[PDB]
């Protein structure tokens, strides 16, 4: 599940590590992690 979410964030133009770190903080909640990165 997590890798697919990282990939979603990378598809938005974010970098893999910043994406992973946002998802970690967000406990896997992609919508929250995206909001962080915007």
Image: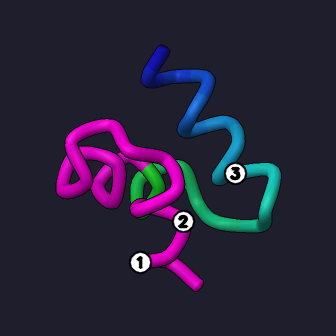
Closest to the observer: 34 or 10? 34
SS for tag 2?
helix
Residue drawn at x 54%, y 65% as measured from the top left? 34
Disc marking residue 34: 2
Please check the rendered image and state whether residue 10 is part of the magenta-colored stretch, yes or no. Answer: no
Query: Above or below — where is 5 with respect to 20?
Result: above
Please check the rendered image and state whether residue 24 is part of the magenta-colored stretch, yes or no. Answer: yes
Give the residue pinned by disc 3.
10
Query: Above or below — where is 35 with respect to 5?
Result: below
Contact (Cβ within 8 Å) of mark 2 with mark 1: yes
Chosen colour scheme: rainbow
User: What range of the chain is rendered magenta?
Assistant: 20-38
Q: CA distance from mark 3 to mark 1?
A: 14 Å
- Left or right of 25? Residue 8 is right
Predominant secondary structure, magenta span: helix
Give the residue pinned by disc 1.
36
């Amino acid at each position: 599940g997590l890798n697919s979410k990282i990939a979603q964030l990378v598809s938005m133009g974010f970098d893999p590590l910043e994406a992973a770190q946002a998802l970690d903080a967000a406990n896997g909640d992609l919508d929250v992690a995206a909001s962080f990165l915007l």
